[PDB]
Image (cartoon, coloured by chain):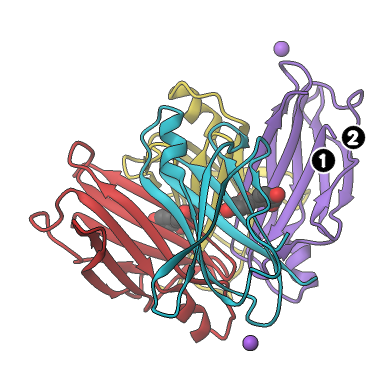
Chain colours: A red, B cyan, C purple, D yellow
Amino acid sequence: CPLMVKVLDAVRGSPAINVAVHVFRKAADDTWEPFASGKTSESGELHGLTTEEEFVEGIYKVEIDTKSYWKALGISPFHEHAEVVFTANDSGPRRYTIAALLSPYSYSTTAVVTNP
Amino acid sequence: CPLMVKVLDAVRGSPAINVAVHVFRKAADDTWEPFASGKTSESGELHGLTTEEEFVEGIYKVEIDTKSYWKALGISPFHEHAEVVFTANDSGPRRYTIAALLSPYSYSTTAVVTNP
Amino acid sequence: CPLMVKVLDAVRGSPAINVAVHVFRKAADDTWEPFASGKTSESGELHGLTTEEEFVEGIYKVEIDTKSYWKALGISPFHEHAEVVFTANDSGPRRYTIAALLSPYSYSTTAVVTNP
Amino acid sequence: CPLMVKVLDAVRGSPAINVAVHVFRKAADDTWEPFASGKTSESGELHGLTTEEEFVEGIYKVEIDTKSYWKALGISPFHEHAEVVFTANDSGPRRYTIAALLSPYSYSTTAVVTNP
Ligand SMILES: O=C(c1ccc(O)cc1O)c1ccc(O)cc1O
Ligand SMILES: O=C(c1ccc(O)cc1O)c1ccc(O)cc1O
Ligand code: NA
Ligand code: NA
């Protein structure tokens, strides 16, 4: 698992379950091409997005559909989505965790990059 | 000010000065049209991006150029930028403050929305 | 202002108004002595806590009464309060802003420290 | 494991390893009594603090020694420590995760409370 996404809910103090997540890779013509996607599990996590072979150096975008998440809870949110844009670099540690902590008008995101 | 951006640096405990900010608005053909840009002052604030007349209903993207900020300070950060995407003024004119708190591998953003 | 506190609400996208704040200073016997208190204004800010003369070197604790804020809004939050503990003025007088961003099960705090 | 603590480093994008953590329980005389302690592991986590039998309803304080962590990295930080104060309540879900994301002048904390 070179890439994992984890999403938490700061209002309820829980994992954010069944949140849609889309990953894109920047193409040579500077457009975003679909790369991988899924929905967070009951632990707020999305595993199995890619493989080491497929996850080469490049610029990636992780788009978390926060608006649908809040609307399903009956809460009007601010953002259309949360976007996390970063470069994957081989010199750095192997495994990337992209974490996001969600509130209706705010989000935090951090990267935990470690060596297996 | 209908739209203001404020940026803080969590490493130095200071405003984030001379941070470039680009604002885009989604056009009728679904592309991101350049809308306004500027850079943060010594107080970490960016005022004067737009006017009440210009700042119509729409979907807006505020791109904060965090990578260039950390690199101009001689540090190699994780993200390319921080993006904040939101619908504005769809219930009439509001004042928006987009605030961000930056670290090299993490950022937080929140919105303060007031009715004049 | 040698010491200012600013508080935002991540659920409502607004300043956090009428939040009680208590400041303490560690005494020579290691106990926490009451130092100053107040509540945030309509802008979410609390000014006038202390003076340059009064705000000597020491270890200070700023207690932000988040539970009472969420409960006065009719919500049951996780934390009792948010505490911010720091040494101040040990290299001479500085200006301190303690900022906090609140959600029912989470909060963020940062400091902006400037030299007059 | 009714109580787990997880600590992340927002500057390096890594778990915060070997961070001292102390847990206290509020006594009837309103003083803080030591309850459990340890150091975070190579994953930034501290497990095994308490048992279901021992972790009764009450007010608890988790104190994370952030100052020593930053000093060991050669970084001058702002806070003496990060403190998280909360009530344990049986009506709510069983397992508490207290997470903290650290920067030199800022920290975020959230609670993830779930049902096994
Ligand atoms: O609360 C967070 C968290 C992160 C990882 C984890 O295993 C558990 C967490 O609660 C968290 C995530 C992203 C962020 O930007 C800030 C956070 O406190
Ligand atoms: O606490 C914050 C804050 C920042 C600027 C300000 O004028 C007031 C604040 O409470 C804050 C704002 C945005 C964010 O992503 C994280 C924060 O702690
Ligand atoms: Na409308
Ligand atoms: Na001194």
SS assignment at label 2: loop
- Residue C74, placed above or below residue C35: below
The chain holding disc 1 is C
Which label's residue is closer to the chain start, 2 or 1?
1
Percent of width and height locating residue C19: 81, 58
Regarding residue A19, the answer to whether it shows in the image is yes
Depth check, front residue: D31 or B64: B64
Kindly identify which residue carries mark 2: C50
Relative horizontal placement of residue C12, taking residue B83 as reference (left or right):
right
- Quadrant placement of the N terminus of chain C: top right
Percent of width and height locating residue D17: 38, 36
**How far is the residue under mark 2 from the one under mark 1?**
10 Å
Residue located farthest toward the left when viewing the structure as drawn: A53
Residue type marked 1: Val
The chain holding disc 2 is C
Residue type marked 2: Thr
**10 Å neighbourhood of mark 2: few (<14), some, or many (≥20)?**
some
Depth check, front residue: B4 or A36: B4
Q: Are marks 2 and 1 in contact (CB under 8 Å)?
A: yes
Relative horizontal placement of residue B106, taking residue A57 as reference (left or right):
right
Relative horizontal placement of residue A59, taking residue D24 as reference (left or right):
left
- Quadrant placement of the C terminus of chain C: top right
Depth check, front residue: D60 or A63: A63
Kindly identify which residue carries mark 1: C23
